[PDB]
Image (tube, rainbow, N blue to C red; front, side):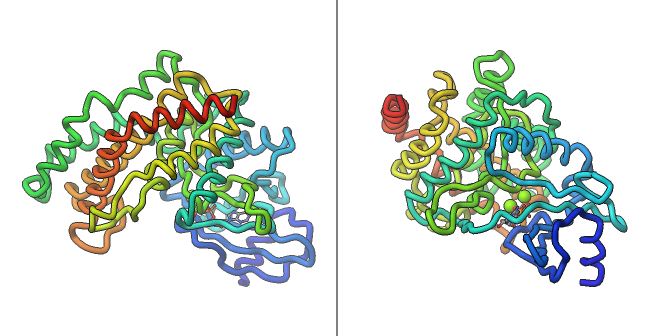
Length: 355
Ligand SMILES: Nc1ncnc2c1ncn2[C@@H]1O[C@H](COP(=O)(O)OP(=O)(O)O)[C@@H](O)[C@H]1O
Ligand SMILES: [Mg+2]
Ligand SMILES: [Mg+2]
């Protein structure tokens, strides 16, 4: 608190500081709530282990937030250092301040389809108002993040190495990913040849990062912009479907409880396409369902790769944790495959309705 107040003094706060306490349930940044005799603020110590290049990350954040503010859209509002920087290095730490976005609630899992539709609307609105932004200006904060062919090379490397001798125990899981190999390059290929628009991508579309109004329930702002990068909005949509349209937790051991919900798929798509109708392309719309397949397979192969490497990337609570996780992702992709007729119809219906 002595140090915290000291850190706070580096920033152009518009109220005398009266308190500073840890805040929120995030686990990458170290997050504090700053109270003043006036407005409130978010103060964060950035994760420089994961994000060593703070200058480039804050440049990305500044570019996107500025575009939104210029257009009168609510977003993260950086509070500058006394020197006019967007962040400060203090005693071997990287710190930044945002205005506290007031009067919101957020979720840690999808409670129901209405909330999921509103999550869809939030990112559709995010995409819509960045549709004119030159996404290529953004640096790749985590290289190859949703480059599924790259992830598959990582997976194959982990399989070849088989450092723990675990491959013997997951042949069906391995064969699932090997057999789908010709599917991984669909979105990367479209970006490279222009058939799929290069857009801003958020890359952590979990609901924790979507603030909704505390009274109306309506989407308010997208936060947690650390992983903002160029890519396809399909990377974001696909991932939201992966975690959000599942009837189960990511590590559900009972696979009979794991299903791909077309109701939740419809809900997100209604919200998302409803805000992005004027910008979304024919090829994009066509790939909405498959984007769910793609990002789910990417995530699943990463879990299985981690299992084979001795669980070095994802936290685990028991020895087979990553294998259990890879299994839910496999189950979800199989249902998405089997429901392709339905989801295609859902998208087509939603597209025409939005007009
Ligand atoms: N500008 C802000 N206004 C209000 N709440 C915020 C703001 N920034 C972050 N939060 C809250 O702090 C939590 C963690 O912050 P976030 O930037 O998502 O960190 P992490 O990268 O660790 O997830 C969020 O889940 C959100 O509830
Ligand atoms: Mg977050
Ligand atoms: Mg984050």
